[PDB]
Length: 187
Length: 187
Ligand SMILES: CCC[C@@H]1OCC(CO)=C1C(=O)O
Ligand SMILES: CCC[C@@H]1OCC(CO)=C1C(=O)O
Image 1 (tube, protein in one colour):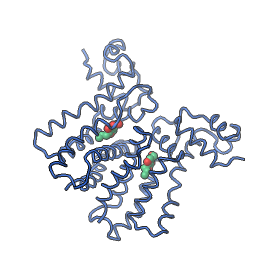
Image 2 (spheres, rainbow over the protein chains, first blue to last red):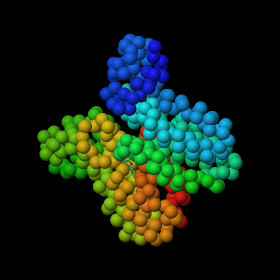
Image 3 (cartoon, protein in one colour):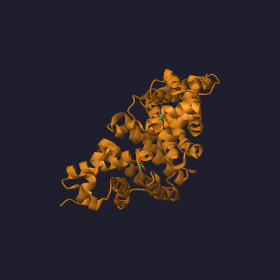
Image 4 (cartoon, rainbow over the protein chains, first blue to last red):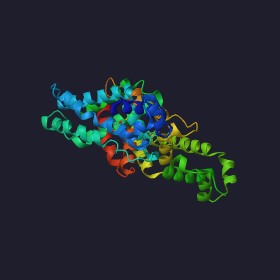
């Protein structure tokens, strides 16, 4: 039988390609192999399905940061590698593409989706605090401000890449912007 | 009688507050003082009205850059002051707020709106080229890349500010990000 993750992947594919309005639970059930009633057991409405997709595209990242940390990357290199991985994931992964598209549509999706930006901001602030204490971060740079700036800039870069080029050029666009941001952050 | 600009301002107010779907020509006509048939003389459909709002929120900026240039600001200070003025304008001006909201909604507005980002990218590239030739721009920084990075980062900053805080904190959010970007751009 199909798992929650399998249903979520199918839902992600459809939301990424069609948006919330154009997606249906009927089409998710067909894609994934099961009846609508069976899907509703896992996700009782289209709204709850959308929420689960957005939540998942955030909740995955703490574990990634832990994987990087235990390899001994410095605080600022940890932030860099997280954003590298995010860029590849928006490029490739339907759950990320769907999470972003659902959040793009938030003003006209009647569903209580998680607040954008704040999870990644909170996530990155921690290594950025360590970077400050360590002497890695340029004097006067506030870690909370750096976290906000990085998340907003990265968000904007990936959004532009999506809107204009379906994220095909995302890695180059991130490289050129990251070079400036990290030049400004490094002591 | 009402001018095109007056109709466009009323339309902007409604689009900014309600989005494209929730806006109507009927409500624009009521707001501005005139019959729907009289409004349709200027803008034959809701689509053409939306296009005019988005086009206007871009077309205004070349003149602003000229006003700054003739005061003798350096190439990089010209870029800085343009983005300062953009931040205040998104904060305050319904036409800017509407332009951004209509572009946010572009994937589900059936209207041929102008491509986002490219006008501002082209606009800023010119002074950034001058900055390079002048020796103002850090060695190795490509002007076209800097223009893209600045537009995407600024876009993201203002979007986050809108989504979370209705742009109330936009000037502070821009200051902290601009400090990093321009630290990285200046020779
Ligand atoms: C560092 C990822 C920033 C990010 O990009 C898309 C998106 C979806 O709203 C984001 C978020 O909410 O944090
Ligand atoms: C420097 C302004 C960047 C900008 O912010 C909102 C928006 C609307 O799509 C933008 C654009 O298209 O260039």
